[PDB]
Image: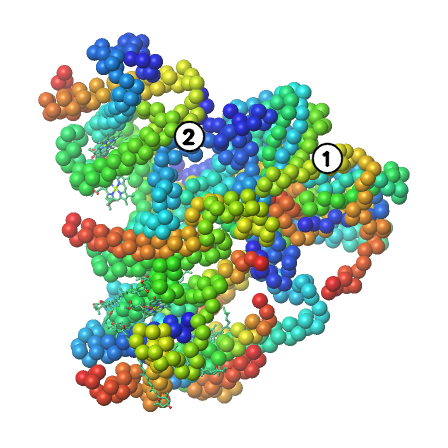
Amino acid sequence: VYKFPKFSKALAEDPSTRRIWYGIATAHDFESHDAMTESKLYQKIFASHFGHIAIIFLWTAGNLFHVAWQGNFEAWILNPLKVRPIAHAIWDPHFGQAAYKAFLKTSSPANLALSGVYEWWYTIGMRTNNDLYQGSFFLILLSSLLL
Amino acid sequence: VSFIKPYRQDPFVGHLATPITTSAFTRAYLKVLPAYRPGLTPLSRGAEIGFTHGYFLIGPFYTYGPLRSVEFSLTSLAAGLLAAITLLLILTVGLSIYGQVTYDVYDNALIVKLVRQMVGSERTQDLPQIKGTSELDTVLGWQKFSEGFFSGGLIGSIVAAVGIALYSTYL
Amino acid sequence: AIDYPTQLSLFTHHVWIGGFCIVGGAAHGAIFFVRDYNAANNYNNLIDRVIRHRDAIISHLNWVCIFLGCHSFGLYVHNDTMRALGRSQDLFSDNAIALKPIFAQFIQNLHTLAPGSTAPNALTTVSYAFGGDVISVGSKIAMMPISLGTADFLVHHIHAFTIHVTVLILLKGVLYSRNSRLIPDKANLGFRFPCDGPGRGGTCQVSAWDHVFLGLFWMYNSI
Amino acid sequence: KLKQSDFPKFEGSTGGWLSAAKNEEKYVIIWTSKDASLFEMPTGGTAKMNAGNNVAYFARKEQCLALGSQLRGFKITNYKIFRIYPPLDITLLHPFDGVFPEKVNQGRSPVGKRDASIGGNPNPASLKFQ
Amino acid sequence: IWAFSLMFLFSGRGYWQELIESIVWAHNKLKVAPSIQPRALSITQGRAVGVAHYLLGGIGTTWAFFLARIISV
Amino acid sequence: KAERWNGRHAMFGWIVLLATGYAQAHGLLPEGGMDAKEWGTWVIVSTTNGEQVTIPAARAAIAIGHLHFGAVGVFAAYSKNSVKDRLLLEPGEKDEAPAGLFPALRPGLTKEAEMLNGRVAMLGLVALVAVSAATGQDILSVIDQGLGGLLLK
Amino acid sequence: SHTVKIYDTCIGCTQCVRACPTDVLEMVPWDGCKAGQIASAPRTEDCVGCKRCETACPTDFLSVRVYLGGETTRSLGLAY
Amino acid sequence: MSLDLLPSFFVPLVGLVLPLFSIIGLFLYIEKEN
Amino acid sequence: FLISWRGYWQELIETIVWAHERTPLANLVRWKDKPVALSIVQARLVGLAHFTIGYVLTYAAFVIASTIGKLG
Amino acid sequence: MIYDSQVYIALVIAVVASVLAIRLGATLYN
Amino acid sequence: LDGMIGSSAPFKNFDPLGFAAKADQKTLNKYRESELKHGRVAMLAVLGWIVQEFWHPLYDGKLSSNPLKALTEVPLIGWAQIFVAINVIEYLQNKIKELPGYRPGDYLGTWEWVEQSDEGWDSYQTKELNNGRLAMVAIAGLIVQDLITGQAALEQITAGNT
Ligand code: CLA
Ligand code: CLA
Ligand code: CLA
Ligand code: CLA
Ligand code: CLA
Ligand SMILES: CCCCCCCC(=O)OCC(=C\C=C\C(C)=C\C=C\C=C(C)\C=C\C=C(/C)C=C=C1C(C)(C)C[C@H](OC(C)=O)C[C@@]1(C)O)/C=C/[C@@]12O[C@]1(C)C[C@@H](O)CC2(C)C
Ligand SMILES: CC(/C=C/C=C(C)/C=C/[C@@]12O[C@]1(C)C[C@@H](O)CC2(C)C)=C\C=C\C=C(C)\C=C\C=C(C)\C=C\[C@@]12O[C@]1(C)C[C@@H](O)CC2(C)C
Ligand SMILES: CC(/C=C/C=C(C)/C=C/[C@@]12O[C@]1(C)C[C@@H](O)CC2(C)C)=C\C=C\C=C(C)\C=C\C=C(C)\C=C\[C@@]12O[C@]1(C)C[C@@H](O)CC2(C)C
Ligand SMILES: CC1=C(C/C=C(\C)CCC[C@H](C)CCC[C@H](C)CCCC(C)C)C(=O)c2ccccc2C1=O
């Protein structure tokens, strides 16, 4: 019932479940935290910005890797108007045989890609599932830099 | 006659002495249960509770699981047994964390008397206060209770699986 | 019977009127408790004893409502997710895990056998809904045996659950209309008041009127 | 029938105090009544006063004060409310100086008084990071 | 009407009172502020309006649906 | 504490790897794949052209054996008051003192002996994985090469 | 616990004190108004935040102001 | 071990084990004292 | 979460608390944080979050499925 | 089709990015 | 044959053979326990006899409506469960019997609330006892008639074998 809202002693003394709920919803309101100065505020915001950019780059790297690994980017290059892009494969134990058959695309059940990443990456000059892997590797390196 | 009266002659408790809360049947039935049966160590209480709970927990998983069989299947029995054992593991994890965050005592029914006699001018909530005097209300007691629950759950689930197999095969 | 618009309209209208009138009865019970209830004149009588254990009633009604809602609606959702996952044999259907309303079918059988056995001076069952022949007037069906299967089981338990939740809201309004652990003097605020304030974590809708408001919503849902 | 002879003739309700008023704090209200009047409990239903000393226990100060406000309708004024901690740590609460808070008594100092109206409050932007 | 009800059911009195404040400012600027001071509906009346509109909208939707369906077929 | 536990597990797993190689060589380790009709679609690995490649039955059996051992470990973890050596440190307990570059040369069933053997086994597993990754053969192939041929014979 | 402040616009009409359900406010001597009394808040630890005190205030924009703050089992009105 | 076994190795791992340990840690942290 | 406000959920939670406190075989387990109803602002936020998430999910499903199923 | 080595080293690099993330997370304090 | 409950108008303190005139309080408590258990079991047995005769929904019909014939038709694994349930119930009753203030047939513990019993409480206890006695006689007659004649209650009555 203590020590969770480390940034707020008023919440940490709450004997109810409201402390847990308000601890989540006030975690990023740095200006209202206990023992707070402006320098610490700007420094924490700066570090949070770095972590956020790292998260964005990791998300993009994950999209690239999953298109390279479980997608049909190379097949979509040769026939972009008939082949439907694949986002990533599906492994869900709750599937029946009918669901597996219906979601089956090429070798495994997979989700069609509605993000338009296939067309975007094709336009900027990507033609191989090894070009996407290089992008994922580089973006994970950039995320490490930002962290 | 009136069969509902204030509990223990206290009209201000949020409780009543109904023919269900304070009936002789209720008294005996709750005093024969493992949680309240006299003469049981916390490990024994946990072991009995786990045995009963795994025994009746394997049932729904085997009967209505994702791998049912109107006939007897070893795969269905194994699936139900594994699901019951993993559920017992989850319950044991919950018991362990609950005991970790709830109590700070290793020997109860004494510390209360010590702080009622030799004063408790400390940070309190460990020397003073202390809710409940049972051996289940200690760090050591609850740890052994969880251990017994977990072991007895495994044993009872296995026993119930064996019984289910025997009933489905020889009947 | 062959004018289907008339039958549908009559049933729906009368059920709506019934639900509204029931919510009104609950509202005026709460109004009586707030205004016309005298504690001295009701010492240790039924009304007093009901208020004295209102907690037990409301808590057990809460448990029953959760049980009924969990079961009925989650069986519906389980059917939906089994169908969406391509597992048609895992549903709560007739060609699957079947929940036959055996008690209602027993009653249906008892009524269709009543003429000549328990109602010996009857020539025909009271209603063909319980069983019998198809009654048609001008090639249009007037009445016919209403078969009860697993689909009727689920919807009947949905009805029971919704009715129980409406009863929960209205009974909580009636019983906690005078006082509570939050506001020990709720009767001094009257039957119709918005709140007691933002304190106590927030005391919105603690009235008894605000319970006839939520109960109106739930009556709409049930009907 | 009851633990103490001064308890009001109440049959007990499942709206009384809970485990909280055994390890955190409980509140007791005492009063003397001329008649065995029938009154409504702040928690449950109807109880009967004693023609003399009356003592009631509750889980909240608000419950005791609601009971006391009800007592004023019976021309009962000498009611006094105490706070009891987990052990017998009795503290007089409501008639703090023997005079009800609505009547001015000498010896009281103003607490939480600001020597200005609402419009004199400082701007929040000047109250940042303190 | 059912969607209209959600304005009263989801909102609160303070916002509407403060909006009526600016509307009253405009009226006073044009010397057309009524003597009967316009106030937002009370909390209880806001709830009552919301529930009445909700019931009317839902019941009317079901009414039209049922009647059209069962008269057509 | 963590080093000691991981060393124990590494030694036991060297034993397990030897047993797995022996079972693969000696006609054990069941053949084929899991039955998707029996165990659902979660055992299906891929569908190349109209046939469902499933998880090998040998992999399932080895996973079941590892599940047995891991369950034993989980029981010992939630059995702290009845085991000789606990998994985690009690509040107050202090971590045994690091052994250093070279633990004391105390032969027998001693703490130093178990410590040294656990370090050796963990280093052996690291070297085995490194050799398999660098050269490109199977783990069991590397063990077979490192035993001359006496394992997969 | 919540914060209750009294402002010198107090006219000493006592309506706040007799409306407090938890005995937080009291009337104390003063020389800033005709009644010679001003409200005080010496027991804010019992303040529940119901704001009945300022619903009974006749002064223009209030003389008793309740600022909700940290919560406590007393301020949350918890009988349990 | 083929690349197509990675989903069956990782999806249960992440989607069940990570919730369990995360719940354990979060519950322990938010239920701490001082 | 938007139509039903607090106060109605605090008394129900109190009834549940009494039920848990007064039942055998479950008295052995007690909460560390007193269960209370969500605050007014928290309730508004939770209702808004449900409203928005449901809105976004249902419209995304509709637009995607309708486009796919209508245009081949 | 990417190889096992390609996926494995990407997983290893992802682990390194994870240890960098907790270091940033712990440095932003409890 | 005491101030015990169960004395009715037709034969007050009915002990023609003097079984209670010499017994101590413990033996009389045992006698009351036996009488109440027999009465309750006999009420259940009579109700089951009749209802089984004109209604046996369980076991997918079958289980011939004549009692003492369905006794040998139950799967004999349902007999074991009924036996075990009765045994557990009587184990609980034995545990009750050592609770302080225990009364011979009182397994509800009414002695906790009923101090200074009324005339209504005594009358209701006597009603239970008399109904139990009538049910004991009725079930004895049922079993004997079904043994000697071979027909059940409503079957023998319907035919007219009286
Ligand atoms: C679709 C919207 C919706 C839903 C689901 C509910 C659900 C419920 N309302 Mg209701 N309510 C609604 C709209 C809704 N309401 C609206 C719009 C209003 C405004 C007037 C109200 C006003 C209202 C009042 C005033 C009251 C309720 C009550 C209840 C509860 C009845 C008990 C019950 O069935 O619990 C069981 C829960 C369900 C049936 C929900 C689905 C649960 C699934 C099917 C099973 C479990 C799923 C599982 C746990 C998921 C785990 C996985 C997950 C962790 C990822 C229930 C939680 C009553 C109450 O407090 O409860 C007694 C009550 O007094 N409601
Ligand atoms: C309340 C609603 C409800 C119910 C009854 C069920 C029931 C079931 N679901 Mg299901 N489901 C639901 C909602 C529900 N679902 C919802 C909302 C979803 C979507 C999130 C799903 C998604 C889902 C999936 C994905 C799957 C199921 C499956 C199943 C089956 C096996 C579940 C299992 O292992 O049981 C475990 C049961 C227990 C551990 C025991 C709980 C019940 C006990 C008996 C209560 C006992 C109370 C007792 C009488 C108290 C008195 C005691 C006395 C001593 C005093 C079963 C038929 C599985 C299946 O394929 O089955 C066909 C499956 O794969 N469900
Ligand atoms: C944010 C980006 C992202 C997202 C949303 C996903 C999403 C998914 N991945 Mg995945 N993946 C990613 C990046 C990402 N991936 C990267 C960069 C790699 C290279 C190492 C992989 C390698 C990978 C494999 C090998 C597999 C998946 C699989 C999956 C699916 C099941 C989840 C799982 O098992 O995760 C497991 C994920 C990993 C082991 C890699 C870690 C993922 C990144 C590096 C962490 C990102 C953290 C994120 C920014 C915030 C974390 C929040 C946390 C604190 C709660 C799911 C669709 C499985 C699948 O396809 O099933 C069908 C599967 O087998 N992923
Ligand atoms: C990423 C999330 C995730 C994943 C991977 C799974 C995975 C699974 N779920 Mg599940 N589930 C989830 C989220 C998830 N769930 C959520 C959020 C809900 C609530 C909405 C459900 C609700 C749900 C229901 C209702 C059911 C499942 C079932 C299943 C199983 C599929 C049925 C089958 O063929 O297995 C068959 C299963 C077996 C043969 C045995 C599996 C038993 C456990 C899982 C094995 C774990 C081993 C573990 C390491 C043991 C530890 C050591 C221990 C011995 C000490 C599978 C294990 C079904 C099932 O199997 O029930 C148990 C089922 O009935 N799930
Ligand atoms: C001494 C009592 C007694 C005994 C030994 C039997 C024995 C039998 N009955 Mg039966 N029955 C009884 C009383 C009894 N009945 C009563 C009082 C009723 C009226 C409700 C019935 C109604 C009944 C029906 C409708 C059917 C049977 C049937 C049967 C046969 C199969 C078992 C079965 O399904 O039971 C079923 C029993 C019930 C459904 C009701 C039992 C309720 C019990 C007696 C009351 C509670 C007992 C409790 C656990 C202990 C008391 C607690 C406390 C006082 C200490 C079996 C020969 C079946 C059969 O094959 O018929 C030929 C059948 O279909 N019985
Ligand atoms: C992985 C193996 C590879 C082999 C390849 C094929 C084999 C296979 O597939 O295996 C899987 C398999 C079976 C595996 C069985 C196993 C591993 C059992 C292990 C049991 C461990 C036990 C009891 C540990 C006890 C430890 C204790 C008490 C540990 C302890 C202590 C002590 C001792 C120190 C004492 C301390 O004392 C104090 C102080 O408490 C306490 C404590 C805790 O510290 C069957 C597989 C298949 O059947 C299936 C699945 C399908 C079939 O169609 C085909 C086959 C037959 C192959
Ligand atoms: C744990 C480990 C191996 C564990 C193996 C186990 C449990 C065995 C498991 C198995 O039995 C099972 C379960 C089942 C079997 O079927 C399979 C196997 C696999 C056989 C290796 C660790 C191997 C760990 C290694 C090699 C660590 C090397 C660390 C170094 C070099 C650190 C250097 C630094 O610390 C300094 C010196 C100074 C710092 O400031 C800077 C840095 C640089 C960080
Ligand atoms: C210890 C070990 C195994 C221990 C096994 C034990 C205890 C088993 C105990 C048992 O109870 C169980 C568990 C189960 C029972 O049923 C069986 C028994 C038997 C009773 C393996 C080590 C195995 C150790 C191995 C494989 C070591 C490999 C080392 C290499 C390759 C070193 C290379 C280098 O040295 C060079 C070449 C040059 C250097 O400069 C650089 C480096 C790199 C350091
Ligand atoms: C809009 C709104 C107001 C403002 C609403 C007002 C001031 C009502 C104005 C009504 C006008 C003045 C008269 C009605 C005019 C209609 C055209 C007549 C009804 C139509 C007939 C066919 C019945 C509130 O006061 C309020 C209070 C609490 C919660 C939500 C709300 C809320 O949403």
Q: Label for residue D95?
A: 1
> Dividing the picture into quarters, in which one does residue K61 lie?
top left
Along the line of sight, the residue nearer the viewer: C202 or F134: F134
x then y, percent, for residue G21: 69, 38
x then y, percent, for residue A52: 58, 74
Numbered disc 1: what chain?
D
Q: Secondary structure at mark 1?
A: loop
Outermost residue on the bottom side: it is: F135
Q: Residues within 10 Å of mark 1 (few under 14, many from 20)?
A: some
Q: Is residue G24 left or right of residue C130?
A: right
- Which residue is drawn at the image coordinates 73% and 35% (left, top)? D95
Along the line of sight, the residue nearer the viewer: B55 or G59: B55
Q: Is residue F30 left or right of residue J18?
A: left
x then y, percent, for residue D18: 54, 40
Residue with the mark numbered 2: B19
Image quadrant containing the N terminus of chain F = bottom left
CA–CA distance between discs 2 and 1? 42 Å
> Does residue K127 appear in the picture of this structure?
yes
> What is the three-letter code of the residue carrying label 1?
Pro
* 2 or 1: mark nearer the eye: 1
Q: Quadrant of ligand 4?
A: bottom left
Image quadrant containing the C terminus of chain F = bottom left
> What is the three-letter code of the residue carrying label 2?
Pro
x then y, percent, for residue A112: 43, 73
- Which residue is drawn at the image coordinates 67% and 39% (left, top)? D91
> Does residue G58 appear in the picture of this structure?
no
Queried on whether the Cβ of the residue with tag 1 lies below 8 angstroms from ligand 1, the answer reads: no
Q: Residues within 10 Å of mark 2 (few under 14, many from 20)?
A: some
> Dividing the picture into quarters, in which one does residue A94 lie?
bottom left
- Which residue is drawn at the image coordinates 34% and 13% (left, top)? K3
